[PDB]
Length: 411
Image (tube, rainbow, N blue to C red; front, side, top):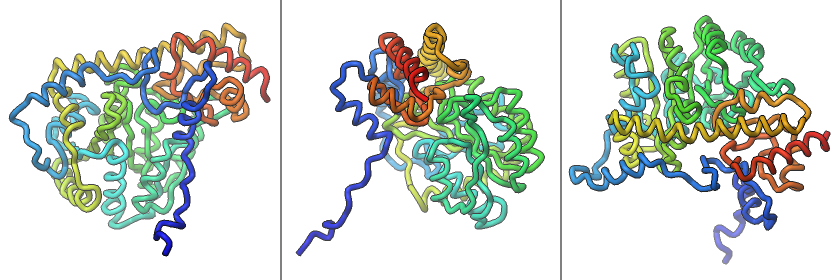
């Protein structure tokens, strides 16, 4: 008889994977991959943070450690350190013991645990109808996680304006003013994915004001703290502002980019509440959620991050390491913009340097992108998104020339 697997179709490849596979295959020597999902150096190589290598040696040599189960909520030192990183050591919320943390399987895991919690205990009990607002566009995992958690009404807020190449603040605010009271708003804390443009601190004040007045629930996604600007405070400004304004909120934290721990899946869900007592109840339910789903947590990534952030000296060394990545990206943005302007490229290019983080919406249209991929062998997404760390001292001129040709030959 036939295999019970005989009619299983070949799954369609996924564009982020296929783009890199196409790059790999390409025999053209000019090829550039601007579609890598991780930081690369000026020589196109992965980068292990020096402080991570040092900490891994310490862990391996620590004979006190065992491999027994962590608490269900995770390694206590990791959770406490991760929360301290977002909020700041002198946060009123930390002083007043109205913070919790839950270790998660990366930032996506933290978003899932939070979503599952909201679907059970927020805005009523077992209320899957609370609207969830995500940016337009956004990281696909925002929509997917909340869908998977059972939320039935996932909505967009206006965010990217392709004409202006920048933030539609008025549309964003308008969409928040029309949000039903108690709707959940998923906010990118800094380094907006996929566009790279963030609200400025004054714009964050306006967003906060509308959220406050309509009792909207902030759910921050903080995937790039420190990695975006090289300055941890700055990168957490909106988060810390929301605390100071009296918000209760969740904040999903990821440590893949800012520790380079892509293959360790280290995340934390920070919870900020009005009062200490109900935080303990919240964590009692998040224990059940973790157990009932996932069940973890794996230790090694968490141990790396805890051992680093808990140690003032390693923490400083790490901030240096992270800043070196951030600074290389910032430099590449500046260099690309300067080269495009020197070529008299049509359009404005301030967006290249107004944006922050590893990803940039270059503002190219899909046909312009198609010219880059197919004629110039520069691999990026049809939205115009590039990984800015794919830019090197060696390829900048080729990329800038190629963009110039795209904008002047196409459309």
